[PDB]
Length: 247
Image 1 (cartoon, rainbow, N blue to C red):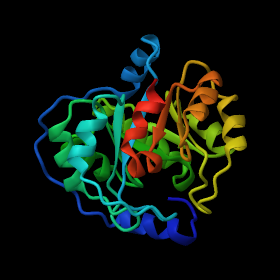
Image 2 (image 1 turned 120 degrees about the horizontal axis):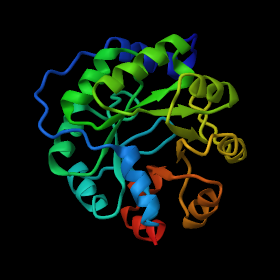
Image 3 (image 1 turned 45 degrees about the vertical axis):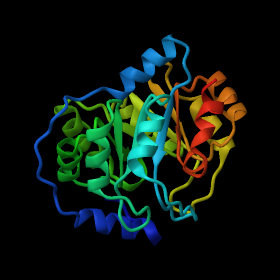
Image 4 (image 1 turned 45 degrees about the horizontal axis):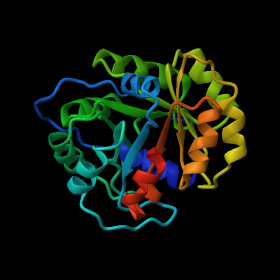
């Protein structure tokens, strides 16, 4: 990985030492990016509901993962499950349970730095994974992208600045996530996010990430060309909001 400091340096060390998970895969892969595209054509707001009990910025919520997922399944285009253990309190078992309970696409959300984590995502039942440009070198990103594709997955490649975007475009990313939150400082910057969204080729599936809590925000982003929205905290605190965001 890249030179990192703070909590990011720590979470990456944890991922490097992450034990692989051996299991048989049941369901075939269900493409998340293709489902977003069809929701787009049916003019249905595409929301990727995320499940996370904790977060380094303060979230601490107790809510059943299965019930939450089964409820979200009625509305969401797909689910995002945190599997990072120390800061988000996620786990592989939680992902495994959920995957066995729902039939919509599942994105495994973690800090992927090695191929075995992608094997884990596939064996656990995930349909795609997140790759973060700012923690990986260009060569690592390119290898991991090809590796995920060998399982038939099109990973969501997350960018936070223009340099991340140059790299993502160079390696041929087709599914990009624009994170308004800077992972290093945990600061949110929606203007930088809006600026980046405007530079992305029209043929790539774009997902707005972080800090969304109101329908009007969704409406504004949609006019910028955003295809889908990844929402976690506001939905963890109030699952009912999914009904507001979707109409």
